[PDB]
Amino acid sequence: QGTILLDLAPEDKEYQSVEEEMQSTIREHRDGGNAGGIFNRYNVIRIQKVVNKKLRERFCHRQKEVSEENHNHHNERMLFHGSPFINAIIHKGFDERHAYIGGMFGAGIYFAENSSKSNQYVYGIGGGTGCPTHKDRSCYICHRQMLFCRVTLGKSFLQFSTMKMAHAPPGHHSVIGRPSVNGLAYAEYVIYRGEQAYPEYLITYQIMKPE
Ligand SMILES: CC1(C)OC(=O)N([C@H]2CC[C@H](c3cnc(N)c(-c4ncccn4)c3)CC2)[C@H]1c1ccccc1
Ligand SMILES: [Zn+2]
Image (tube, rainbow, N blue to C red; front, side, top):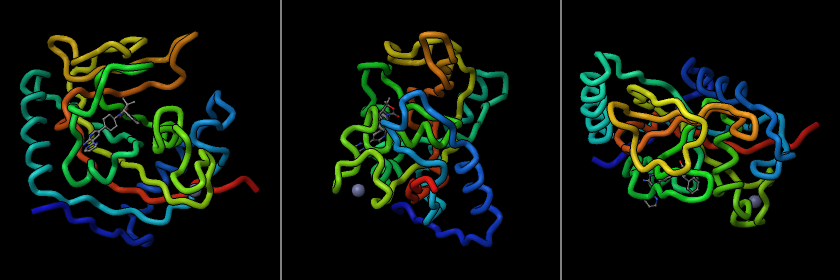
């Protein structure tokens, strides 16, 4: 009924596959490490498959709708997501009702192809005040969580800024904020319907200090 978390073993190719994507999508960010910490690698301590009959089924039902309106192409894609609400997400699914127009963001759920981008948000916008125990955005002690999700993008509307969007434009199912000068540095994939993202993998890790 609820969700069941399935431990993958490091010997399992799926485990290796998921970690590789994470480690390899670490990229340098213009903030000197202020948001997600200074690190050149992660210590992946755990990777669990998220199994939830209800959620999978809703996700599949939505994927079919988007498909009929996108010429039978649901445009599914694997993307990362980091936020202080992962534990809620893996049990109740993504819920746009917690997405609000504010600051540099529209009322949608944001994803990223780069694991280090998602890491910048695990403790809040701009990293917030860091981990709860040491209030350190660069804590190497506390364990972090991020999701490698299945994301139904359907027909994406491309634009430079995504901060005052309430829903995907007419005819579309997602919005991609693209790089610009004086703008974004990495593309941001946004959905406005929770059902368009299934949290396939729960990644437990720590950023490692440089050597
Ligand atoms: C900047 C935004 C646009 O990028 C996101 O992806 N955000 C999501 C993160 C998670 C959130 C969310 C999505 N699904 C949920 N299910 C819950 C959630 N929270 C509390 C209780 C129950 N559920 C929260 C909505 C916006 C936002 C966000 C908000 C605050 C911190 C980090 C990230
Ligand atoms: Zn800490």
